[PDB]
Length: 384
Ligand SMILES: [Cl-]
Image 1 (spheres, rainbow, N blue to C red):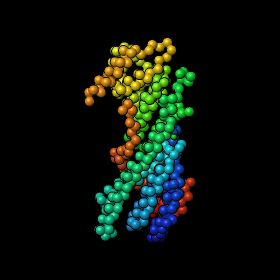
Image 2: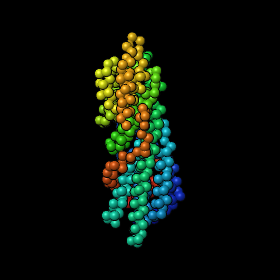
Image 3: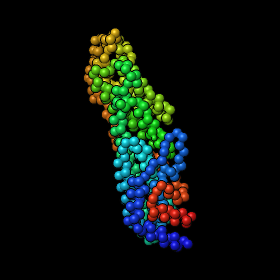
Image 4: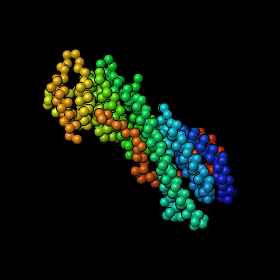
């Protein structure tokens, strides 16, 4: 009976005390991410199950005109999701962050869809006014949420790289003995971003933005460490740096990026500088063309700090003064560090068309224990 289903639905939805607690503590804070990787085939419903559940609840509240209940519910949802992303850390950081990006994108896409449906197809006409106004604000709130959690997450990713990439790129020996975190750890990290985004059906533009931002970041912070080191830069260190950096560049090539080489140019060009001949004037003129991303002052620091090995010819004084003169020259034509980009960053989701919404069957997973929420979804499902 439609009326009995409607009455029961109505009482479930007006009882926001019980419902908000279920949603915020059980569904949102209690989220479980599905597995990601090469042999994994996830349906979209396994990835965005929290968003789809929220969408069912939300729309039922609107259908019954529980506009005040929806506002209460939504404020809790917005706060909780942002809070959840703020608390992400450790091994879970990449999959949980991508998970929440997917879900907030699904929510935002729904609201965009609902707003267009309201304006196009659709009890006081002044209540309708307040309604359009509510959904419009909700669209802005989810846009802000997406931006916020994208930036919160991306900053946490940068810090994990500040922690690992410097040791892996600059310090760890690709050739042990030649001269904690290794390039393998760095590759694992970027692979995890790749496979979580792939498996969780994330739009490729977003993958491009995230990884380009992080590669530029690795480039800046590792370069800055390298250029301060005064008893370290040498041919051997250059060969090892080459092997570390090339591995990251080759990963970029097989994982959809064509601009990875451009993001790593300061590291790549430093490795070259550390390896090529630095003995004649022409050597230096050639080196300048190879190192087109390095300033003369940077060339000078790197060259003047270069450490010759036993049986290796010293860099001649003639060449050191040539370089110093190129620096004093270009100075007379009016930092050595690269400023790391720390944001905030444009939300790459905001640049692409939203998910066109096809109405999907009411579904709520099995490990969940959400009595009211599950009854709502079951009752909605019965009306179909
Ligand atoms: Cl992973």
